Amino acid sequence: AQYEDGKQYTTLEKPVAGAPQVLEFFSFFCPHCYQFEEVLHISDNVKKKLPEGVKMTKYHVNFMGGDLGKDLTQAWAVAMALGVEDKVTVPLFEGVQKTQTIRSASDIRDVFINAGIKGEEYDAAWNSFVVKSLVAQQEKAAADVQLRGVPAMFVNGKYQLNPQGMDTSNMDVFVQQYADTVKYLSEK
């Protein structure tokens, strides 16, 4: 075929019932994730080719960067609850990997503040049980697929994107192939 299992994607031997339709995992410590977000804009180019009616979900993971890694998953929960993902994603990446000014939970907080979220609102969210359960959801989904690496994308809880098996000579062509594969898998 043109899309072969084991080539542009792999199939989970343990399919995950009721999983989000498009599920992406990342870490603000993950160098390829930085690329995926700020250079390739993967999430965006997938959405642009997804059918109508398919929701897109993106979760942070704990297994990189120790304590600060967990702080970032809780902050990503805050980001999701307040709907401010598009305002903090870039400074979190650059704060962690570019400028290295993120060294503590308080430095993570500064990014939200600088992005215009108010102190009280952040701290209230940070401490809220809605955020606790949003953290739990992020962990459960990563648990459900044995996740030990990022970036990672899963479609319908059955198929996992395999970027190692796509041409990387051209970044535009890589992204289109990636997105087209998600669309294929999505219609499967």
Image (tube, rainbow, N blue to C red):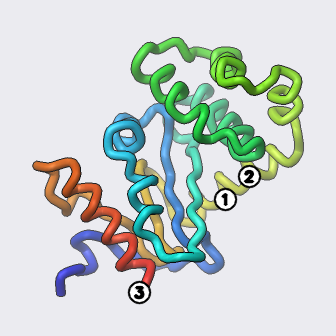
Residue 34 found in image quarter: top left
**Numbered tag placed on residue 188 in the rendering:** 3
Badge 3: how crowded within 10 Å, few (<14), some, or many (20+)?
few
Q: List the single residue furthest toward the left.
A: 169
Q: Label 3's element?
A: loop
The residue tagged 1 is 140
Q: Residue 111, position in %: x, y?
A: 63, 21
Q: Which of the two marks, 3 or 1, is nearer to us in this view?
A: 3
**Numbered tag placed on residue 126 in the rendering:** none
Q: Residue 78, position in %: x, y?
A: 74, 38
Q: Label 2's element?
A: helix
In the rendered structure, the answer to whether residue 75 lies left or right of residue 24 reads right
Q: Residue at x 71, y 20 (%)?
A: 113
Q: Which of the two marks, 2 or 3, is nearer to us in this view?
A: 3
Q: CA distance from mark 2 to mark 3?
A: 29 Å
Q: CA distance from mark 2 to mark 1?
A: 6 Å
